[PDB]
Amino acid sequence: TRHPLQNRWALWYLKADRNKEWEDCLKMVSLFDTVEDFWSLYNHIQSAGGLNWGSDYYLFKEGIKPMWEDVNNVQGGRWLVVVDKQKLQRRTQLLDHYWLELLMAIVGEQFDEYGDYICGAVVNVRQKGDKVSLWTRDATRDDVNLRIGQVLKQKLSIPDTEILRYEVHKDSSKPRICL
Amino acid sequence: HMIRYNRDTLMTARDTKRAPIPDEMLQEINRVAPDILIA
C-alpha cells in the first residue's frame, strides 16, 4: 500500500547529554513521505512521553533545518503549548496526545489552505514543563498564523481557557498573538 | 494539488497496518539513534 504525503518530512532527535552543546546532540533520524513510512517510524521510536528529560523531537519539512536561524524560519515564529498543570501519568498522556495529534495534523495537511506556511513542530521534554510548538514561516501574516492557531487548538482539544502564545523567533534573540 | 489525510484516515491506516518497517529505515534509526529504537 502507498499513500503519498503532500510533503517530505524529516524527524530530528535531540539526545540529552549534559556535556555537549545543542548542535552536537542533534541527529536527523529519518525522512519519510508516505503515510506508511510515517507510521513505521512513529511505531518504532520512543514516544515523546518515553524520552529522558532534556530530549527533543523535531519534525520539519525536508530542507528546513530545525533552528530559527534557518532562512525558512528566520522571519517566522511558533505557536507554543506548555504542558505543566497535570502530574505524572496524566501529564505524560496529555503530552503524547498533543504531540501525535500535532504530527497527524501536519503530515495530513490539515491546516486549511495554509500548509505552505507550516515549517515544523517541536516537542521539548522538560521536568519543569514540556513544550509543544508549531513553527510557521512568516510572522507578519496574522491571517495565516491566527487560522493555524485555531486549527491547532481544535485538533489538540486545547480549552478556550488556556491561552496559546504566538512568539516571533527574532524577538527571542511578549507574544504577537494570543489565543 | 493538495493531498490531505484526516485523523480517521491516518489512524485507520495505523490500526490496519501489517507491513513491517523498511529495513533501510530501521538501519538508519539504529545507526544515528539506537537509544530511541523500539521493537
Image (spheres, coloured by chain):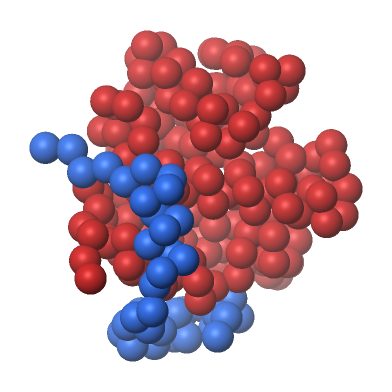
Chain colours: A red, B blue
Quadrant of residue A109 within the rendered picture: top left
As drawn, is A49 to the left or to the right of A139?
Answer: right
Observer able to see residue A80: yes
As drawn, is A113 to the left or to the right of A12?
Answer: left
Picture coordinates of residue A105, whole percent (x, y): 43, 42
Residue closest to the far left: B1
Q: Return the residue nearer the eye: B34 or B12.
A: B12
Picture coordinates of residue A101, whole percent (x, y): 53, 45
Does residue A60 sit above or below A85 in this rendering? below
As drawn, is A24 to the left or to the right of A96?
Answer: left
Identify which residue is drawn at 45% across, 36% down: A135
As drawn, is A43 to the left or to the right of A21?
Answer: left
Q: Return the residue nearer the eye: A65 or A108.
A: A108
Q: How many marks?
A: 0
Identify which residue is drawn at 61% across, 22% down: A165
Picture coordinates of residue A115, whole percent (x, y): 30, 33
Q: From the image, which quarter does the C terminus of chain B lie in?
A: bottom right
Picture coordinates of residue B14, whole percent (x, y): 43, 64
Identify which residue is drawn at 55% across, 80% down: B37
Quadrant of residue A38 within the rendered picture: bottom left
Identify which residue is drawn at 60% across, 14% down: A178
Does residue A25 sit above or below B33 in this rendering? above
Q: From the image, which quarter does the N terminus of chain B lie in?
A: top left
Observer able to see residue A60: no
